[PDB]
Image (tube, coloured by chain):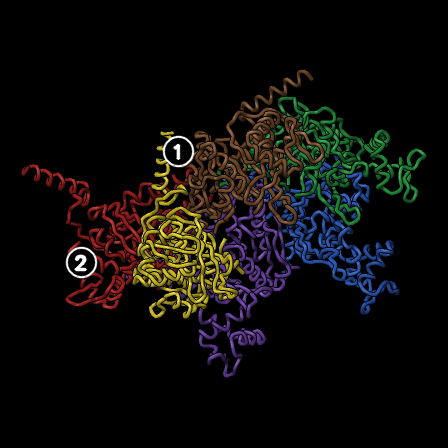
Chain colours: A green, B brown, C yellow, D blue, E purple, F red
Amino acid sequence: DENKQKALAAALGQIEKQFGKGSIMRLGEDRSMDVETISTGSLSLDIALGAGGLPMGRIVEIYGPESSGKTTLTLQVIAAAQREGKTCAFIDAEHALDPIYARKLGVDIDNLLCSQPDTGEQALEICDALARSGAVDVIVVDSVAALTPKAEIEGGDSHMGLAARMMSQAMRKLAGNLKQSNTLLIFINQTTTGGNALKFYASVRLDIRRIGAVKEGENVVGSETRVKVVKNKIAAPFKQAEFQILYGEGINFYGELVDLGVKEKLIEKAGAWYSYKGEKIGQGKANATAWLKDNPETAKEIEKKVRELLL
Amino acid sequence: DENKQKALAAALGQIEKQFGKGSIMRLGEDRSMDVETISTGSLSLDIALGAGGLPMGRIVEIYGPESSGKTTLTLQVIAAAQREGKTCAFIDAEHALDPIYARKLGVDIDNLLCSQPDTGEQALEICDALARSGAVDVIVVDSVAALTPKAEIEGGDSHMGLAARMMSQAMRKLAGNLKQSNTLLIFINQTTTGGNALKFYASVRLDIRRIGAVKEGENVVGSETRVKVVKNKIAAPFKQAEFQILYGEGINFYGELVDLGVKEKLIEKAGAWYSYKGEKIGQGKANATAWLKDNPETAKEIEKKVRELLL
Amino acid sequence: DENKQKALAAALGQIEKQFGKGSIMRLGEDRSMDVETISTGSLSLDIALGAGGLPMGRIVEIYGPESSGKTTLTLQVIAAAQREGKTCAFIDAEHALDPIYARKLGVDIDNLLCSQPDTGEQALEICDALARSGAVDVIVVDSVAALTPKAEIEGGDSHMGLAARMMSQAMRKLAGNLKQSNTLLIFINQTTTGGNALKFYASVRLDIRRIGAVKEGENVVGSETRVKVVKNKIAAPFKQAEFQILYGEGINFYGELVDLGVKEKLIEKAGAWYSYKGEKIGQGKANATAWLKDNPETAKEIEKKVRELLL
Amino acid sequence: DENKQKALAAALGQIEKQFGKGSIMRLGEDRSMDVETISTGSLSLDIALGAGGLPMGRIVEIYGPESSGKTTLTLQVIAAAQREGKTCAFIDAEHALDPIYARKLGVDIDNLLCSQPDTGEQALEICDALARSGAVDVIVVDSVAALTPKAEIEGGDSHMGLAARMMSQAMRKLAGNLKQSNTLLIFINQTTTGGNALKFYASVRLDIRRIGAVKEGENVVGSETRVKVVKNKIAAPFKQAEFQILYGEGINFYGELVDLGVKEKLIEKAGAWYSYKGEKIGQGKANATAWLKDNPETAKEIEKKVRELLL
Amino acid sequence: DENKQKALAAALGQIEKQFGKGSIMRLGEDRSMDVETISTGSLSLDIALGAGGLPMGRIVEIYGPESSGKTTLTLQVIAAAQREGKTCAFIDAEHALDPIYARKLGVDIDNLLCSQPDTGEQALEICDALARSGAVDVIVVDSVAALTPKAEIEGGDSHMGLAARMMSQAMRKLAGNLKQSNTLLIFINQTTTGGNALKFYASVRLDIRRIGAVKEGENVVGSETRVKVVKNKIAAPFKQAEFQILYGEGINFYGELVDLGVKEKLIEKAGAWYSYKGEKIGQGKANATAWLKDNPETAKEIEKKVRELLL
Amino acid sequence: DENKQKALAAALGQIEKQFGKGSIMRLGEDRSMDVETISTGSLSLDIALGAGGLPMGRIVEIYGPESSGKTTLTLQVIAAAQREGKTCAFIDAEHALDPIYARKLGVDIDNLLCSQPDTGEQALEICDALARSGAVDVIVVDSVAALTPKAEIEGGDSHMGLAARMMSQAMRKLAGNLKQSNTLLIFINQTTTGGNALKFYASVRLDIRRIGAVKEGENVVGSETRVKVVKNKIAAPFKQAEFQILYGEGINFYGELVDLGVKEKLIEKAGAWYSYKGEKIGQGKANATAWLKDNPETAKEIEKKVRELLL
């Protein structure tokens, strides 16, 4: 028993040593790698990620059905990054970016770098060139399924096979260059298309889905969302997050803060009343949310505490 | 910071150098490629395009639902071109051209070249032959969905797959020939039909939709229209334009000039009164519009200024 | 400029050469292919067709809503043909021919060949057999939508898809045989049903519609009609014709002659009086019309002149 | 006859001696090897296995279609093991573990070791490292088809051939190390993928399939399941088990106990009434099941007896 | 002529003498070697074999596509053997034996010896050990293609070549040992896999195929089967047999008896009525079959007679 | 010139004298050795052979791809021989004889001697024993590629080299014995396998191939066949024959007779009508063929004449 524990700890260390940090973990583990991260815009998701956000210098995949919120998430990541002075690039093969919505989410469109590549290979080569430049902090690719191989664009080989080979031939180099420059790259996808390269090179894989609607009376104002961290090499995987994505607003962060604040016993709740530091902040989640939103500095205080407690 | 900026500018230059001009841009960029362009008939759209119109020698796709204004736009382009002495050709597979409406828009029907091809392949081959002739300045294809592959016309292969292969097998050659002769080619479409060839070979892709009706009392006189530049390789993409398309008249250009003139502080507006150069031009947008329409030379003056300021 | 024109003329010639006569035309072109034609019964339509009537040896489609005049037109074509000694056949799948009305239009019912096929395929095979015989000059098929595929008649495949395949599998052969024997074939239809085969194999496609009623006081005596030549491979397309179809009489030819005679300055009109060759022919269109109708030989003189001037 | 029997018994002993225990058996044999085992969560399956569960220190393969219950079984094995204080590891290449469902099945997620390997080879090497540590009691690999060879991940060799060679090159070593440390390893699969290595090195191979649904009225609450022991080197093979897998609950163990208890004449059944030790336990299988579930200690008594009688 | 015949008979005798019994035969020959045999479960096949069944002490190969009935046949052989008190062994490398179906065919599963070898070589060595024991009467190997050579299991040599060498290196010894102990061994296969050893060492080779389905109304109840004796060293080869294999029942023996009984004029047939010994046994083959099945002793009488007449 | 001719004739005679009859020939030579022959079943082939069939006492090789007709030919030879009272033997190493098809070709299966040898060497030794018996007239070996050397059957020497040595070590003796007893031996093969022994010892070598299909409407009823006499020591080589092999019938002899009869001006052909001896035998080759087939005695008359004229 005593010897076994040491034997276990020793074997796990050897694994980590031989195959790399994160190669194996106890799912209940509280420890998490030391890496710089960018918020996803969601507090519950940042917590599910263990590290407090998406890891810099790594590859991340976010996949889910159309209208699941995949794009909202990546825009929220771009917004948070830019807010810190980071340079972001959007590699577009979907031709569907909504700048009006992006601005509402806080994205600095004017300073967002954008590329609309001629082929899937070119898209990947541009991602690699940007990764090597060491002058770009975040790259978002929309999307894997839209990265049509040159051979297909030129019109008898399997389109699936061609896409898989295209992704494979570029992944190792890209991953190395991204790591070296500490650049984060997110692939939006819809097993997912593109083969096994992304699945294995990704440090984080997120499964996002719309699980319901958010209504204010009888009017649909958004969607209830659920994100599962199906792969996580920086912390324990399989945690999930649930939050709302409101139209023209994005992720309802303060709504999350209210709930987490309560769960962490930082915010008291007597019936329909919420209180913080011996003072009512609002009656009803809607009001408590509005309060925090109106009192930014106090919200930050609670968030910092929620993070210190759960991360 | 100082070094990073240079590193960024350097990397972006290398991208442009290796993959081509327009391969990447800062969305807030004011700079735009040096290319000859033809007006779309809409001032707001010419502005959204960044270059002041559609680029000569390139492929453009305009797609949207039936009755969205797709055809009105292409006719306006033909009209503007012919007005400059350019030769235009209309490749028809829809058999729906309305010459009466076209004339009202200013199209010189008598001098418009027209082809009603026997198959989708033939349509493409004729476009290529015209592109190589170097004697045609603008080609409009109506429409991609109507370009039925010979195999389908002759009546077990996927009709979608066949159309995609038909477009793919002709695109590279067509694009090269169009570029060499500086011929503009617009594909009207309704992701769009035809596969990935057009999507990637296009230098500009326009999403057009009818967003409402225009009424003069209780009578519908036209449609409020919105065009989004979803792809743009000559200038920053994702800009949008809104204008009216009036029955028997076409795009309400002067109505746009009034609004843009005001926004650019070139035309003063006191309540319902509009003034230019210390003189009232009309009370109410309808009158201001009518004024400009009646005073052509002055309108040109304002437009030239609006263009110099926004392009 | 000088060189360009030659370059243009040269390219267009190559197109015509490579893809066939009529593959491309300047809409204002006055030139028209050299083909034998049969009158439609309408002078304005014969003029809109450019060649002076429907082309022998080709496939023609006439489509429009129920009660638009589709059948009246085909009967008028049969009448004109028979009047020249040509043999006509009516392939019927509608079972709605009105012999009383047909006779009033001048159709020689006694000598009209008629077939009421067992299936859509059989109908097409009979058309092909008649086309190969070289003993039939005009074939009218009523109608495409009624040509039910055998599979459907026998009662899970798309009825639309089946009809499209039925038409496709027979069109090439039919077109070749019709061309070889110089037989004209008209398909009456109601995009139209039957798929893309007819749309592309047709040398002429006519869109006919009833745009109003013709009244003599308060009694409806006929319909104002409009025919648009949406496809024309023998002359410039998109021209239109407007005429009246009177009950128990058919197309008001003389009414057209009056108007065209006037437009062509062949018939003078002082107020309500019409004159020809220094003599009043009638006061009021109704009288002028009646005059021409009563003076056949003179009408022919005017028509011959109108044709020489406009064709 | 008398001599033959001895000759037979002697030959079979020599086989067992020369090729190993379990090399040959009389299918009706009641005897079973002496090995430590972990329950599968199903009583009927533990019985079909002959030894009362899956054998420690051996390799086991569980294969079947998607949604057949493969994962439910392995989770049930992990749960039972952990319940005895054993350390379990989950090697994941599918990225689909549902921790909520796992907990419902009794899995101690917090203490479950998890690895999400970079390649199929790495997955196997980690399994071997864990096997040599002697500090892990159960390893589950999900799944064989997802263990993509490095060569394939890196993108012209047969993917099937590569996977087969990958499994082959690691199997002997793994099997020896697992045997030496008495570690059980289960490969989840879907002949199965991976070649012949697993098929021959496995001491037990299970074919699992969903044969129907379980309904409570009109609502589907689970699936009727059937497991066939297609290979068994610890006891006679080809026995089968049938049980229910209920959503959010897992294998319906008590439902099995009821039936087996009855079959073994340990539980009397008069019509719809079930009785044990001269007392009614419930009317209807649903109630009898609920009873046992509520009276844990008594259930154990019956199970112990069923096992002593059938194993 | 007279001398030639003697010369022929003399030469053939010398061949038989020098190369072995069965080395040459006149295909119409009625004579057959004197060897103990086990029924195949099919009367027509036992007849085609000439000796009345498969020969003890010899090697037999049964090959055909998947679902051809190969396994049904070997199970029928095992059943017949066991019914006579013979000991049978099943060497399994396919892991697909269906004990439920086997029992329905009459196989005594409880007393069936079974081995699931670790390698193809081990499988062969176990067959040899059992052959030398002289305590096993019938051995069935399922199947040749599944006997993976150790070298292949361990993962650059031709898999085909390796399998051929594996079979070759074991065949002579096996054949000698089987002959010495009078043990019958059947190899199930799918030219066939395994090289030339089996092809030449086999005394009998059977080609079995499903040639159609057996239906009772509109429900498929079995398969029409055809077996060709492509090699036969105990009697004239190239004879064939046709019979039905019914699901959950096996070979329709009585259906064969009915037909053969009729052909041999042992059973009279007047229209749809069958009679035996001056009494109707049934109207329709289905009834006649059912009769014989219900009157076992009488069936035996007919079979014994059919055999005496045709063997 | 005069002297040269004599010198030539003299030298050629010396060659024939020193090296053997047939050692050299003028390809246009009409003369042919005096040897007994058996028909091939094809009239055109018997003619191409020069001697009217295959030579008794000699070795013949017939090679071609699978399904080329090799077996059909040898069966036709066996049939013709047996029809003359000759004794035939079939040495089988392929185990693929189809007795049903053979009978249709006229083969007397009941009296056909058959051997299915244990090794390639044994096959050859049996052929030699039969050759020495002087009681067998025709021997067919199917096939050379299937005559596996004992060494190979027993499983590091070249399989090709071993087969070549096996054939070589037996050929001289076999050829001498066959010659002495006047026995014909045909080796079926697929340069061909077996080395150089057969190639040089053969008096005739036939290259047979399927060059197309024979259809009766849209149903394939047979194969168009072409046989080239690549080696011929009894008459001039390199002649070819073309005929049809119909399923379930064999070589279309009468179809050949019709054509040859016509070519030899023995059968007149006026358009589609064929006549013989001043009487129509049929309209169309199919009918003329059927006629001859129905009038055996007359066919023989024509064949005898065709042979006298061309042999």
Residue closest to the far top:
B2
Quadrant housing residue B234: top right
> Relative to E21, is B247 on the left or the right?
right
The chain containing the residue under callout 1 comes to: B
Q: Residues within 10 Å of mark 2 (few under 14, many from 20)?
A: many
| E46 vs B157, nearest the viewer | B157
Residue drawn where x is 33% and y is 47% of the image: C33
Q: Is residue E284 visible?
A: yes
Residue D161 point in image, percent of width and height: 55, 40
Q: Nearer the viewer, mark 2 or mark 1?
A: 1
Residue drawn where x is 74% and y is 42% of the image: A226
Q: Is residue A16 visible?
A: no
Disc 2 element: helix
Quadrant housing residue B128: top left
Residue closest to the far right:
A278
Q: What residue is shown with label 1? A: B133
Residue E28 point in image, percent of width and height: 37, 64
Determine contact: label 2, label 1, CB under 8 Å: no
Residue D205 point in image, percent of width and height: 66, 48
Residue closest to the far bottom:
E278
Residue drawn where x is 69% and y is 48% of the image: D70
Task: Tell me which amino acid carries mark 1.
Answer: Ser
| D177 vs F42, nearest the viewer | F42
Disc 1 element: helix
Q: What residue is shown with label 2? A: F306
> Are the residues under badges 2 and 1 in a single subunit?
no
Residue C160 point in image, percent of width and height: 51, 57
Q: Residues within 10 Å of mark 1 (few under 14, many from 20)?
A: many
